[PDB]
Image (spheres, coloured by chain):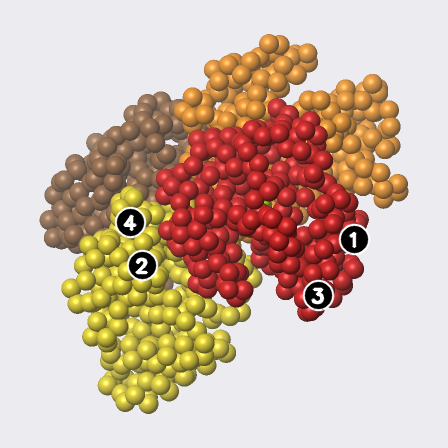
Chain colours: A red, B orange, C yellow, D brown
Amino acid sequence: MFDKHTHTLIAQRLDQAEKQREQIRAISLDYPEITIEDAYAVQREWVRLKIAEGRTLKGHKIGLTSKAMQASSQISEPDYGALLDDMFFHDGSDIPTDRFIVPRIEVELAFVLAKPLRGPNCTLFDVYNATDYVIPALELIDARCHNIDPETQRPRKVFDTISDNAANAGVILGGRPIKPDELDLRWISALMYRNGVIEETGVAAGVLNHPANGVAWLANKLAPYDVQLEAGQIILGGSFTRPVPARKGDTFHVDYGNMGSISCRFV
Amino acid sequence: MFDKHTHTLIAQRLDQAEKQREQIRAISLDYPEITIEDAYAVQREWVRLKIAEGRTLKGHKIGLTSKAMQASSQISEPDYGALLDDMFFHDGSDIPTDRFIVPRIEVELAFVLAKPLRGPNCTLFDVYNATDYVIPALELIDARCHNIDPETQRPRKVFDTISDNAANAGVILGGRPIKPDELDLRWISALMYRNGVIEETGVAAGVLNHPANGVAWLANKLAPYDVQLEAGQIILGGSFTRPVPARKGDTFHVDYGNMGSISCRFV
Amino acid sequence: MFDKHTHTLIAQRLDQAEKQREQIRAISLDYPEITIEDAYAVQREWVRLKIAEGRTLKGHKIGLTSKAMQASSQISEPDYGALLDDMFFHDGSDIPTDRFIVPRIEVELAFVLAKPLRGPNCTLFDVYNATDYVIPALELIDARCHNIDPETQRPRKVFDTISDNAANAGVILGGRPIKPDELDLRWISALMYRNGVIEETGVAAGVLNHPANGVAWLANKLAPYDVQLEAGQIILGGSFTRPVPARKGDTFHVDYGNMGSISCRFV
Amino acid sequence: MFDKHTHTLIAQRLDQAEKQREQIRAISLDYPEITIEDAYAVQREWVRLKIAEGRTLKGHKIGLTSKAMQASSQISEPDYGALLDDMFFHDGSDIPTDRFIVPRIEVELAFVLAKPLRGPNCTLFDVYNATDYVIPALELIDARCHNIDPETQRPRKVFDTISDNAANAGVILGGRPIKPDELDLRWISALMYRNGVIEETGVAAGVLNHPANGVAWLANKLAPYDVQLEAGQIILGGSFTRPVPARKGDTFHVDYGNMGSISCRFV
Ligand SMILES: [Mg+2]
Ligand SMILES: [Mg+2]
Ligand SMILES: [Mg+2]
Ligand SMILES: [Mg+2]
């Protein structure tokens, strides 16, 4: 494990990559001895830097939820990253494509907390008690590191993703807010349209068998750092679709059936 | 368009590939001038051979329904193949892995016809009127041609798949039979488990915007050949999930919610 | 009744049996005058030892919840055991078969407590008041004593099972969490699949007429020992199916209908 | 295979066994080379004799509808028997215990045919088309052959059960008649009470994955004998519970929830 100053240097390089919209070499290639603990330490430093610049923490996301993507990576559980205020775009918004590098859209559910959640021993049941509203949410993900020879599996890529604030870039909330007990969250389903054609469909149970499961897991991950999920935070639970590339000119419309819809346009 | 003898020659080679469980070189590589008309002519010949051997036509399938698949296959419409009696396995069956080469499982809805459907001008409404029951159905697909050839590493094409009876191999019907009008077919959703873990999820609208659409399209495609979809036939409308590889020892469970489930095990 | 030292030494022998995956002779054959209270004292010592090793108490289970199972065990009421943190597996997990001796799977409902339950005079209504959520739960049960005695061929007795922490080994929570008032718990039903075939089915009322009844009974049983069911504990109420053997390679899928599903694979 | 005369004489012996309520030696022990087809031939002769006496065929039952029951019977498919008019008792009837030898109660769904079903190629969909109503049904089963051989202690075999008209003795229809399309038959569930205590519970999908599947299977089994399922016949599809012994003084109550109940008392 590296000393903090190494984590800070890597964070500064990610920060410049984001600002210039120019990718850097995969962190795990430049730092072949990097550990998962180092990766989260890099993330923490970068988030710290971005908050010092004037951003505010608004929540978190859980990623790498599919067992398939978990299997091919160096780890055997999901990942997480921090959501900042400048990542949020309004339902129906024009999104500036130029701000991103290789943006892709994911289909998720978000949990808006009424009460804090703290580990250890946080459970699904604690999540239900603490959740004010569940609402559909799109995530816009991106990559500040190059991915060389993408067809060749390289498990240590997960360290890059984690360092790179779990690929965070954007969030679009929309549709129908519900109390968590209103209906069975496992069977919420969605159709993702891009430019008027369905590109992906999915069902929420594809996220960790229950789309709220990652929230409890996250609270438990954060506990050792003396961090909790705070009241008012928005927690994105994970995607039940493969991400779909967003290009300038694209319009997205994601239909969650009786849970409403979310739209945006890339300009 | 190749001569009658050449179609039969290709069909016999596909037939040998299936019987021996030994893939042949892509048809498009040995025959670079192959057209889509040729491909269907080859399929017809192979089906003729297999019926002459003692099999019976039980229905048809529609494939290449997604936008991802149509673009990558370089085609602007779906494909189709013929379903024979020996392709059908019972719900909950042991499936002999050794019978197949590279089997993969798809998640579909099947339409069981009470009345014939004939083109041209077959509509979605005709399909509703002619359908006795809709039932969940898994398709087991396979490939008798190499995906990447030993000699040149060149990829397999859409002509190869179509010639190869649209990748047909197996069908597993199960779950809950319904009249077409019982509920909105567009929103039927499914969770595909392999070995207890969700590998894919999907919603039926991902099949041509309405899972009955392919049935009408198919009747219209067959009209020129003086062929119709016959009463009693089972028509598989297309997959709302990417295919998932089946290996010896795998248990599949596909949960269609209020439409029931289908299971099998590869032995 | 035996002295405290004997309870401790029997518990140590069971602990070694579990650790080494090697069964010991039925305790009741070595100790012909063993009482039900002795059996619970052995259980308490074993739980104490495991907690001393760093384990944490997470809840309890109730067993022998059929009049038929009670008759076979020559007892007139259920039994209970303690659930420790290391017994819990995630929904969809690989379960290490080598960790167990003769594992079997049961189908249950779990009660997650928001408030403590203390005897005497704990009622069904107290259980409803104290329960935060009900969630489907599988129990993985095992046996550290021989069922058929190597020397005498005589069978294991209820004293052996109770001493052996009521056959406890594993727990798998999954599916849909509900408030106890959401629907009639009595009519929750389930299909247990092993390797894609239904091995057992059952309905929750098969557990003591109402799956919450065992929880009240348990609180009342524990009162004389100055023990109560604590807030945050998970209480498994009993199986509505006969247990089904788990072997290496087995995939389990348990379908509780509108209450969701739980799966796992033995590896 | 035995000659026709032997089938007749075995049937006469079973007929006397039933009349006298005195078991005979297991047929398979007297006839070690007995085949499944011999067993069905004995059954056919017995049915013929009973009809000659003035009885009328009212339908059929399907048995051994579990993979587990099939394994115990060393068979790879269900069995069947014929239901005669004098086997039917009214809901809430006193049942004369003295008429039977070792009676046991099973919990089933019955299919009342509006149209005939003939093999080969009878499907689930044909069953739905031909079924007028589905109604809960209890089966009273019995055994005219010793389970444990007086001389050798050897057990009864499947050939014995099939010869013995598939253990047929009584049928009790009751509860709520529904059109097959009214609800999902797979999820009909039941609680069997004997003397006010639940002895078994079960769900209809436990019968061959779908309680109508046995009906199609049966039509296909009967086709080679130039027999079909006739309009107006009642077909019992299989038990979703293990049979429960009936003794003089026993009251049975079987609760199918929203499908109604069936009761009887043994006197
Ligand atoms: Mg995401
Ligand atoms: Mg298909
Ligand atoms: Mg249990
Ligand atoms: Mg029966």
Q: Residue at x 72, y 52 (%)?
A: A14
Q: Are marks 3 and 4 on the same chain?
A: no
Circle nearer the viewer, 2 or 1: 1
Q: CA distance from mark 3 to mark 4?
A: 52 Å
Q: Which x, y percent locates residue B227?
A: 63, 15
Q: CA distance from mark 2 to mark 4?
A: 11 Å
Chain label for disc 3? A
For disc 3, the marked residue is A5
Q: CA distance from mark 1 to mark 3?
A: 19 Å
Q: Earlier in the sequence, mark 1 or mark 3?
A: 3
The answer to whether D248 appears left or right of A213 in the picture is left
Q: Amino acid at mark 1?
A: Arg
Circle nearer the viewer, 3 or 4: 3
Q: Amino acid at mark 4?
A: Pro
Circle nearer the viewer, 1 or 3: 3
Between residue B163 and residue D87, name the one nearer to us.
Answer: B163
- Residue B138 found in image quarter: top right
Q: Residue at x 77, y 19 (%)?
A: B37
For disc 2, the marked residue is C113
Q: Secondary structure at mark 2?
A: strand
Q: Amino acid at mark 2?
A: Leu
Between residue D72 and residue B168, name the one nearer to us.
Answer: B168
Circle nearer the viewer, 4 or 1: 1
- Residue A107 found in image quarter: top right
For disc 4, the marked residue is C180
